[PDB]
Length: 185
Length: 200
Figure (cartoon, rainbow over the protein chains, first blue to last red):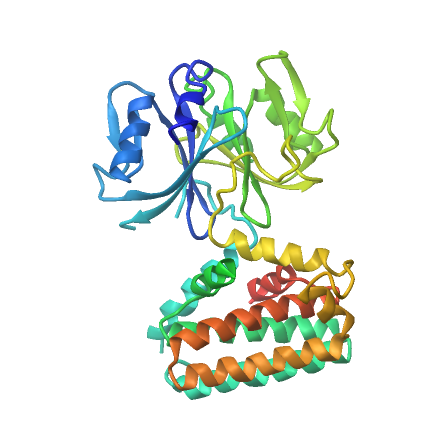
């Protein structure tokens, strides 16, 4: 970062660096904005995404007019030091690209849908009964693989994931916590 | 991209070169930022391959023209002000010029790790039993892999039932790891599972 910032190709970008902002957990791409060297210093120092208006006037912190700020987790250049990628966590309530989404994003959204259905008209049956579904789906999953029924295996693996996400939510965890736990190993 | 969407693209704001974010259509990894002129975008759409306009060489080029690493277009969409496109794409070989994947150092969104773990576990179908825990699992055969799943389902269930949030995190991690290997063992993958989940 003391090295990286000098090497930024400010000349090639006309002092206006393109910055991709991406959700730090889910990988959803949120926006492209533009940073001058000041914007980047303020971003680094504040920990909030700060841009510089291409259109006309001034630095602006993302959210300074709405409450919808982006907390920086990481910033990295590409190979030619002419684009930044910022991983950020949004605060205040998805991203500017219509309904396009990378396939695995659906698992992350599914988890959000299952969390909201705590309050619809499985969760009410209590931890033990949610747990019983995992355990019995693990059995089914094991048997379907073992007889090489790939179609059954897919559907049981799918029920297993579904129920595991519910089980995690029930105990105030989530799949992000598991994934991070795997990353630490 | 619809007819009217292309009509509304803000080419003047961008000086006739639209910024285009290229993202891996499955994993979510951001691969690169490039630029298209209108023709670059038209060939991208017609060809199914990501085609930029190199302001340096002053021509169209299909990413992969000199490396073989092409990008198969899955989807294209504008941001809400029509001055950036997002292209979801499936690479045909690894995308960046120093052997790796994307341009952006080792930074990744947190869920990318699960995708990466899966790919590691898939590579090790080759590797021989002493090369890794995974290769050893694969050599033990389907039934032993499935036994670990069933056992980890039982453990995950019990750890939840007694409200040990620490053990549940760990047992659920073990469950995920082994589930990935079992799917790979049966020539499936988590992508295929996520699709089935999506279908409901």
